[PDB]
Image (cartoon, rainbow, N blue to C red):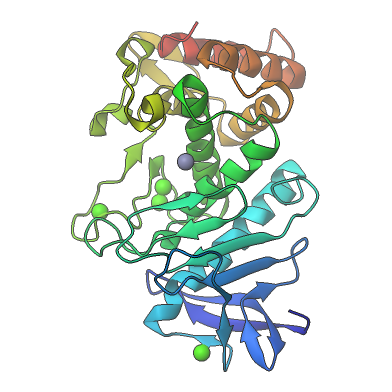
Length: 316
Ligand SMILES: [Ca+2]
Ligand SMILES: [Ca+2]
Ligand SMILES: [Ca+2]
Ligand SMILES: [Ca+2]
Ligand SMILES: [Zn+2]
């Protein structure tokens, strides 16, 4: 829509108040013109046709409970866009400022969120397993990082490449959560997963085995479910990424952590310059070693920690 940029205020899924960038033209729309070619949020109105209607509001105030998921989708897409721009110098997911689109209230009782190839889609949850999925900044950044992967390495969504694709999304979703300093942690989806239980989450990067995911290459899932285990075997990479950052001893192998910032520089580099559509875990290891080598030198501590981390999860 063509109109005047302005700022509205609302409340997100967890009840927190925030300012959001809106556009005025008769109504106030959720259209942020301050970032790239824009961030646009749509109402799918409980249907599955996409994208739905650009979200329109009469007074620029978004405190209705129906508004909550739109507020957070719109706001967290802007925070993810800022993370990629400021930290990695990348302009939107394609690197050329592509418009970012999201639809909320997709279907009824839908317990998922996803990047479909052209935009982000978020269900409201059934209210028991999940509350509206856009309330989780790690979930929003996870889905938006799939768009980044799609335009760069192009990892196919199955078997080891799909597991890497998923791990990349959990790593950058977590790094975005630390960037916004929103009670950060190494768990995924804990702000929106099971509102009746405290403490749990969908997946853990610091201890994937907590929920039954593998944390070692010898425990990988080799069946056919979940497209060959893309959400299961990602735990091996997540654990390696946690160790590179934080350090620790895992199955007897000691890793000195080098921190989150270096972790994000090494993996962003591996992702945008060395990973290809069919890369497997062993190729991920070699891409990560080469990336740290490029950035810090072959006899740096950084290269040494990437190697120990992959040795600790059994990836050679
Ligand atoms: Ca309103
Ligand atoms: Ca958190
Ligand atoms: Ca988290
Ligand atoms: Ca919970
Ligand atoms: Zn994913």
